[PDB]
Amino acid sequence: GVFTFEDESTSTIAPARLYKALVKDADAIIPKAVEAIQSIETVEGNGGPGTIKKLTLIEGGETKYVLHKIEAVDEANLRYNYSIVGGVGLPDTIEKISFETKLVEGANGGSIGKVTIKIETKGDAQPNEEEGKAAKARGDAFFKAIENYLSAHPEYN
Ligand code: NA
């Protein structure tokens, strides 16, 4: 099945600037933004749609990886879609989790990040709370964790 829900966040950072870092500078930021994430390596492609990347991370005593795919990039509308693909770093009941993000200008000039998350399951029961939280968390590296690191960084203050 497919479990779809919406998430919204804010940033003090102007949307074009935030968007640019999300789509151009992820590889450099993410291992600095997330203590557990050791490295990101691009496996196939150049940063546009179809690109596959491997995140190497430590969770408990175990070195694991997830694969990330860039689904869509539309700079004119500040749209960035991506997914984490079925396996080592997702719960067993989950084939894929996609994040569909759009950045929009807040009234006061910061950003509102509008996200639709789609969790694809093997079965006919929506994921239990933890397995969905764990899957969502894998996707945070690519959006929320970057906005967080940037908001505390000298260049975006
Ligand atoms: Na790290």
Image: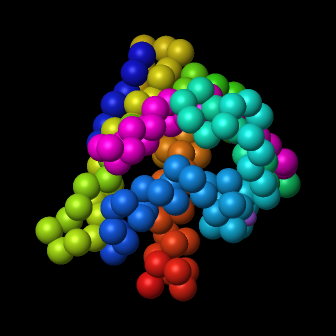
Q: Residue at x 59, y 26 (%)?
A: 50
| 121 relative to 75, above or below | above
* Residue that lies at the very extreme toward the front in this rendered image: 76
Residue 71 included in the magenta stretch of the image: yes
Q: Position of residue 131 (x, y in %)?
A: 53, 38
The stretch of residues the image draws in magenta is: 62-85
The N terminus sits in image quarter: top left
Decide if residue 66 is on the left or right side of residue 23: right
- Quarter of the image for residue 42 reads top right
Residue 56 included in the magenta stretch of the image: no
Q: Quadrant of ligand 1?
A: bottom right
**Residue toward you, 61 or 42:** 42
- Coloring basis for residues: rainbow
- Residue 128 visible in this rendered orientation of the protein: no
Q: Position of residue 8 (x, y in %)?
A: 30, 54
Q: Position of residue 74 (x, y in %)?
A: 39, 38
Q: Residue at x 37, y 27 (%)?
A: 3
**Residue toward you, 119 or 42:** 42
Q: Position of residue 62 (x, y in %)?
A: 84, 49
Q: Residue at x 73, y 30 (%)?
A: 44
Q: Residue at x 73, y 57 (%)?
A: 37
Decide if residue 62 is on the left or right side of residue 50: right
- Residue 133 visible in this rendered orientation of the protein: yes
- Quarter of the image for residue 85 reads top right
The C terminus sits in image quarter: bottom left
